[PDB]
Image 1 (cartoon, rainbow, N blue to C red):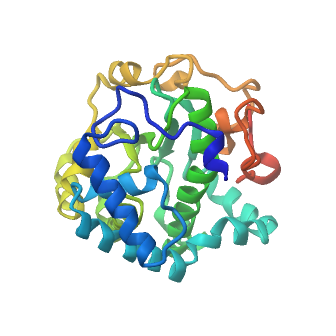
Image 2 (cartoon, one colour; image 1 turned 90 degrees about the horizontal axis):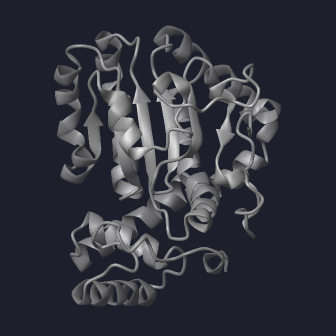
Length: 307
């Protein structure tokens, strides 16, 4: 299997409960957890990385972890997550056309990695015109896009970044740029944010590495109080709302050469005419780190910037 072509143990200096950094009791819980799922006849996604993510999300309470894993398998099957990349590929032409329309208005792109080797993810909400967005896309479509990325993240980005880091990478480093948004719109999209939180927390536990929110307007703390209610304790702890010193905070976690110039870094596209919202640069593009899983599909079609 592909799991054999990249590190399956995290850095020895990663958080507790991660692959290769278990206590005796955690190691035993894992074996018992996998034993129960095997007995229930599950076959897929029973690797240490996956199972430990569920165990951590439930504090190694085995039965509560089994319930969570069982529900996730059902959901993946009913929602179509198990074939989402395949389905996308079978209709690439059309999906890419739709994707390119929203790219400039709602930038979502990966750009290298943080200091621990985690994929560096950026999203800018400032140029979003809700009226125009509802006219060209739907919330369900965007949720689909989210689920597809979780799958792309696991099959392409993780193996590549892990081979480059020399150890298992299970999470990402996300930067949410809120410069230019209206709190008004923020409140208007609460239900969508709630849907994102539910998919993430229920079916993709422990995928959050670092989550920074920069350029948030005054009074964002108020609106965020509306969001915390449906976020789990661990999720909140991974979210950091930065102030005017955000650049110094980002530079502690991200190599300056990987950080875009406008965020305090020195990273520039090889062609200062390409747009960051059409880019997908990272280890998953380096032939030296791409394995039997093959290279990740190009989300922005012919426009996809791979440098």
